Image (cartoon, rainbow, N blue to C red; front, side, top):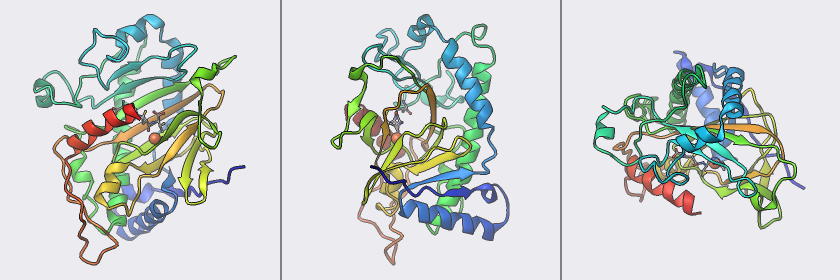
Length: 325
Ligand SMILES: CC(C)[C@@H](NC(=O)[C@H](CCS)NC(=O)CCC[C@H](N)C(=O)O)C(=O)O
Ligand SMILES: [Fe+3]
C-alpha cells in the first residue's frame, strides 16, 4: 500500500512580524518543502478555522435546491451567462457527488473598472438571500480578507525563499484587483454511493478528482480531518496526512513557470472517501495584468528561457484547460 508523504508543519507566524532573521528561517523551510514533495502545513496562521468550518457547514446544510438553481453558474443554468466562475456548482445525484460555491474578490462590484469593461475572469459575486442565510455573506467576505492576509504573509516567505525581497510576489497581490477565489466544497456521505460518481486511477485507486496541477500562484487550503489527498513523487503517489488545524499549502503552475520549475506545481489527486466533509481552497491569483519576469534560482545569472506571461492570460487559459482535462 501507500507511503505517507513528507508534509512538514511550518510555523509561519514570523512572516507577520518584523524579525527578519526569523523570517529567513521560515523561508528556508518553505524552500525545502517546495523542493521536496511540494506541500507543507502552515501552522500558527492566526485564522479561526473552526468557526470557518461551522459557518460553511451551516450554509451547505441549509441551502435548498431552489436556491442552488438561482445561484448556479452557466454550466448549470443557461440564464446566467455572466456566471462563469462565481456561484453554485450543483451535484448531479447518481452521477456527480460533489457540489460547491465559489466567490471572488468582494471588491468586484458593479462599478469596478474591470467589471465595467467585462474583462474575462472578473465577475460580481452572487449570494443567497440574507434572511435565509443570516450573516453568511458578511462572514464569507471577511473570510476572504482573513485568508488574503495569510496568503500575503506566505508570499513574503516564498519571495525570501527564492532570494528576492519580501514584496516580490505580494506587490502584485492587491485587494483592489486580485483574481483570487474561495471555493466552499461539500463532499457528501452517500449510501449507496453511485459508482458513476467515482473515478478510477490507472493504479486502481478510487478517486473523486483526477490528477492535476493547480491553476494558481499558490493554493491555501483548509480541509476536514479526513485523509484524502495524494501527491505524486518519484516514489509514486503518497498520502498527505490530514490536519484540520493547519492550512495545506502548495504551488500552482504559475509559480512553476516563474521559477523555471525550481518550485514545481505538484501533481495531486483526491481519493474517493465516503464521508461528509469540507474542502475550502483559496486559490492565490494575482491581477489581470500582473507579469513577473521568469527567472531560475539554480542558474548563476538567474536567467530563464521562458517568456513572460500575464496572470490574466495564464488564468483564462488554465481554468478552461482544467475543465477540459
Ligand atoms: C485539488 C482539486 C481536485 C480541487 N481543487 C482544485 O485544485 C480544482 C482544480 C479543478 S476543479 N478546483 C478548481 O480549479 C475549480 C475552482 C476554480 C474556481 N472555480 C476559480 O475559477 O477560481 C477540486 O476542485 O476538487
Ligand atoms: Fe488541486
